[PDB]
Length: 107
Ligand SMILES: CO[C@H]1C[C@@H]2CC[C@@H](C)[C@@](O)(O2)C(=O)C(=O)N2CCCC[C@H]2C(=O)O[C@H]([C@H](C)C[C@@H]2CC[C@@H](O)[C@H](OC)C2)CC(=O)[C@H](C)/C=C(\C)[C@@H](O)[C@@H](OC)C(=O)[C@H](C)C[C@H](C)/C=C/C=C/C=C/1C
Image (cartoon, rainbow, N blue to C red; front, side):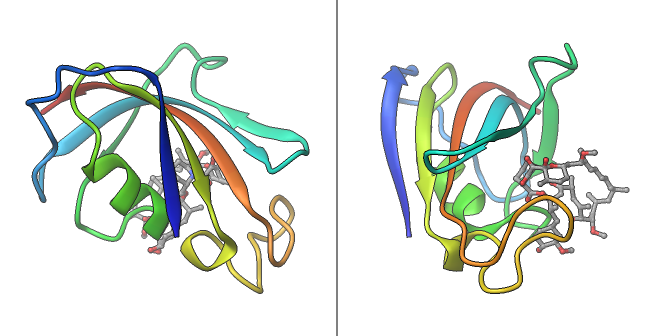
């Protein structure tokens, strides 16, 4: 599944709805491995629409339980991420992913 551990609390009231755009910053790394991506480096926040299957399942379920302002460590098992195939060139088969995700804003 996806485990959500809080780094800094959000407001505890404003949670994403299906169909809303979540605006986030993230850093991704392989569990006890390499950092492979960060929107912070790029100075540009990542946006995705919750519930449209644009992103991996662990993000869909993980971000849905976060409130605005929250920063959390998401640990995502391979079956909630890229599974036995991985993501070619970047994520190997059967990788556990850890993301640091900060929910900035909803649009
Ligand atoms: C350059 O950076 C990439 C993101 C990179 C790619 C490689 C991975 C390691 C990674 O580094 O991100 C990464 O850290 C990662 O694993 N992410 C990104 C952050 C959210 C979680 C995860 C992810 O789900 O990636 C996604 C993962 C790689 C693929 C998806 C996994 C779930 C599955 O349901 C989807 O099937 C459809 C495919 C990539 C994304 O988050 C982007 C936004 C979404 C898509 C490409 C598809 O959903 C696409 O389908 C046609 C769409 O509907 C989109 C919106 C259409 C518009 C025009 C395309 C925008 C493309 C943006 C691409 C971006 C910023």
